[PDB]
Length: 159
Length: 159
Image: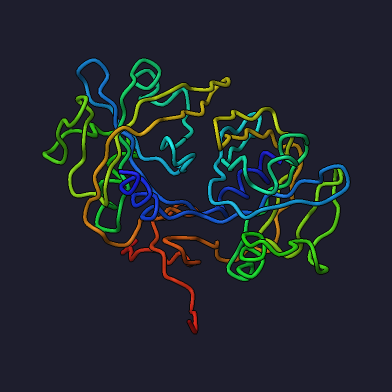
């Protein structure tokens, strides 16, 4: 049952984004599969994270964040931002609006103000209102499913 | 900018689930691309929906709901549950635990109790604690991206 729940989400595919935050001068960021649209007017999105993430204190104590949509050419960056090594070592980012860390060469990004976090024991829902953004290079979205990075192939359609 | 936000989520792929609820005897349900894992202990998931959904009153006023993970063989059911026709016309479901409508032949389902909804002007975040579930037939997950149902193909790996 702990099993059934973990299993069913193993079977649920997801798109891959990266969240960035500048916590009093130091950049933090992390790969995320829970980013979802919430509303259009005003524009908002949500994601979930663990309060044990190395980035939780940055998120708890900061207002502006970035979200980055990833394509297939961004798989290395996705893996970077999911592992424990220093994620900002390299020339792959720079500070943008509100001093949010902006990652180069992504499908596009949005900058938001965190409205609130809804915190449970070990995880939180984060609600963000979007204040800025920029479309990047169009490409094929990056997906993650049962532990592997994947690409979407549309299903046959006669049209 | 209304554009940039709508565009960036066009570029963000997603897995496809269906949410079902029994509102005082009548089944309601809807296809959803925002279902995400929140926590493991206790097990919880989140999704977002529009307060103008035909299913909002069911969700606002009911506690038990079902979520169904979909495979490629479930594309017709996904489309059913996204369109305005009577979604429960046919022999493709039955009442399960807590009288939740359970859809047949899916990748698996979970039953949850809605803890709360966080309601904005036109949309809400719904937080659900999982109380029951069952793995269905393993298969390939269904994805939805820029208006089309897709399948995930893993990216090449030398291993």
